[PDB]
Image 1 (cartoon, rainbow over the protein chains, first blue to last red):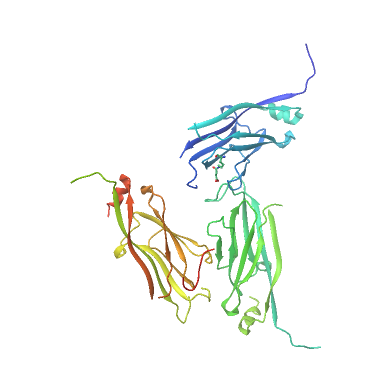
Image 2 (image 1 turned 90 degrees about the vertical axis):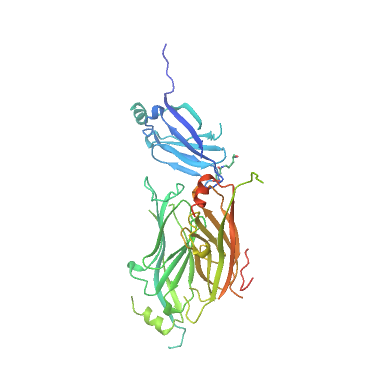
Amino acid sequence: GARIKTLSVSRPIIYGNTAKKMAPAEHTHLWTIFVRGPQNEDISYFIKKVVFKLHDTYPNPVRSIEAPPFELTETGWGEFDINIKVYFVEEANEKVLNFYHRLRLHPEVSSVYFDEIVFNEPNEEFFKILMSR
Amino acid sequence: GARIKTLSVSRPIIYGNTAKKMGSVKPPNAPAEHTHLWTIFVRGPQNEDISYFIKKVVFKLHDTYPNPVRSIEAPPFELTETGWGEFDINIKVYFVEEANEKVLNFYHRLRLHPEVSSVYFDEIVFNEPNEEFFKILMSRG
Amino acid sequence: GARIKTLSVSRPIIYGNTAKKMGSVKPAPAEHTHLWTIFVRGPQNEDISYFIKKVVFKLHDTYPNPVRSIEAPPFELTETGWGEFDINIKVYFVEEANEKVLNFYHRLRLHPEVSSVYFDEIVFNEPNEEFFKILMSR
Amino acid sequence: IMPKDIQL
């Protein structure tokens, strides 16, 4: 059979954090939060910037990463929710993609997710960009 | 008509700050939180010399900065730093020793967000200056 | 007799301040009436930098940049002033020590040349083998 | 506030 359906295009994505026991003396761990592609392939062709919002105890908790690799390394002692905002390239004409990640420091410790970003009703130009691989 | 009045001499002055969001390349020793480069300054019109009546300018930064008291004792009377937040910078103008004057104290709100700039073009008014400092002021440089 | 005991190693230290009333000609705010120097040194002024990396003197909040970090010998600072106050002294040991900061303080003395100087010792308990080698290097 | 007088 055949039917008309809303256009949908998916892009695989890997995100999360790594951490290791080792800057204020209070901090006990070094950790790095990230958003990347599978096999570490480029994702900047459809992602313009990634903003990580850290705990309010950090100076300027809003950390904007505007070029790949979309990651940041910091020091700390406690686990907390890191807000992740993914901004797409301007051709997409898309709202910011908002989610969050539980920073894991305790059992090198790692907390990594391998999901996909689903784009519904993308415009023709952004569709061209997505199909450009 | 004619009358006796307190002597007053004015000197035009320009002060304030410039700023720009930093790209990929940050200066050495710059904390990662910082997003902007900015310069606070006190200068003359057309960038003409003001050191003939100004000995030094002291900028007091936020206490989050290491050694917040930044003393500039030679022209250009300016300081360039990095930062992420807007705050009030205290400015102390010290005049040359001939003036026998108290420190001139004021402040400026650092502007980073809409190159962004916040610049004022005012004048310093000297009331009852002594004869020697008057000679210096009238020297036009 | 013989017994096992916690390892302890002592290093003689001299610390405190000197002061002098300023003369006709001043260095400097007009308010200031005294010149004074706060210091931490060894006996006979022998080097102490082999186990001391830096010394931080925190002055009264009336002073510009009250946190004064001296990261090379002589571990001292000379300033001008009018009033007596408590100076916080933090001694940082060389990285080999793996030691917490040594915290104490000294009351700046200007009035009865005036001096306030102590000749004590720093006691290191349970030092590691590396820092022990450094301490024994004399 | 920390004390600072001519003489403590």
